[PDB]
Length: 566
Image 1: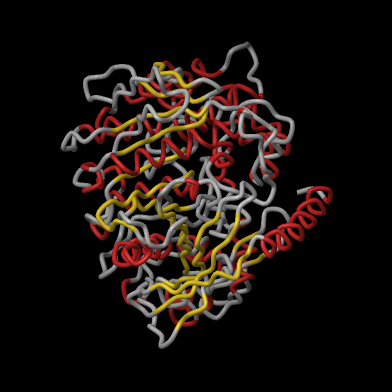
Image 2 (image 1 turned 120 degrees about the horizontal axis):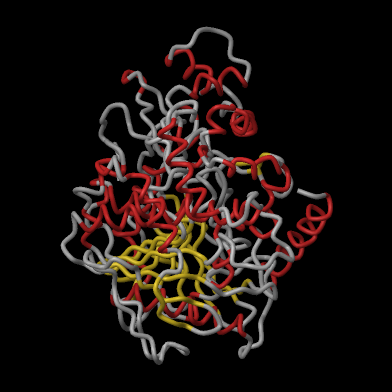
């Protein structure tokens, strides 16, 4: 990231600290929790609203020392009143702006927000799980401020969980108790805390909605798949991702050794000696080296992250993924709760930064073999069956005689988001009680209001609705500003928080109280549907057949001979 954006970010970071201070009030309050009393504080918003804020509530023991790489343990309760008037650090990660490692291993916290601590009626509880590829992210209000949602009568909770190798190391040897998915286990525990404690904050423990974007969407899906969480919540919203996405899991058991060797380990490849090195290493050191872990072969095969959710090689007490997510969908309790899913209208625009640094990536579309689903493709992607399959992708996304950067980005929309969504929907319909799934398509384009991701994806001055562009209309961030109430941006904030709150409340995203929805007849998706319908969200709200359907079916054709793998 440029020196320019670094300076601009630093200045915005300073202005955020002064504005945070300015918007703080003297109204501290005390709430009960299972683990003891917590003190929060009322805060203000730039729209002249206010909310109670409890940050730094621990839902697990700090996973430091011997607890590193291990499943989370319950936290130690305290006497007296715990200070929750300030946020804790984020998980150890590479800051994408400065490029330096930041955060702390002491990261297992959640924040609770509401505009009214003593509601006369119990409120829907929305739980947000941030994205960031399972390697970055946080619940700090400079990125995920509750300022918009607290105009609604909900309780909003934002969680943290372990990222990168510290959250997703996996070792084969059962003796060492490092099977994997520590970060997902963090989420499980946090949902358990929320179920047993939201009532103390005016929440309805029997009406909980989990939602997340990107890896947060994959995370929400996992929390709907795993047995560990059965009945812990009541609605799910998957924004631009799910657990069947190719980036959403990886068999990484052989990568621990590689990490250790990048970090100076001397000795043999066996899990015990590798773990003993990794657990003594500086956490910053491990996280800064993670980027170099993937082989050239893995990158060619579109493995995006070296450590992430994995199938656990053995089943322990806290096991979350005992088999592949595709198999887990077959008995998943979450199939039987109201669900909403969606994407933006140009997801792949997110890879602009990558394509700028490696223009030779566009050449991959001459055959498209590299994008054939890994389970169908051969190792070298030289087999005639792989060339065949690649050709089907190629016909879907190459518009001319030579591929263009735009062809690449459009392809990415499908490879990373739309096709996995299709696969999940069809797989799911063969194992559901008939509870509804609703689809949206976020299609609202503006640069009058933006979020930090636009900086990372080099999206400044770039038209189209990229992956993460919708976040801007859900959460406050330190690049935001007060918008005029009749602006298209302010109306989109109202619509998006309005739809999400309505869904959270009833399991049905439609309401006539939401401006622009007057003609909307928003049906769910049915198993018998050959074409998906979605609420397209732009300056107008309109029900349309999913435009991406044609390319979606072309990708599905790759499985003509291998239907069991679809």
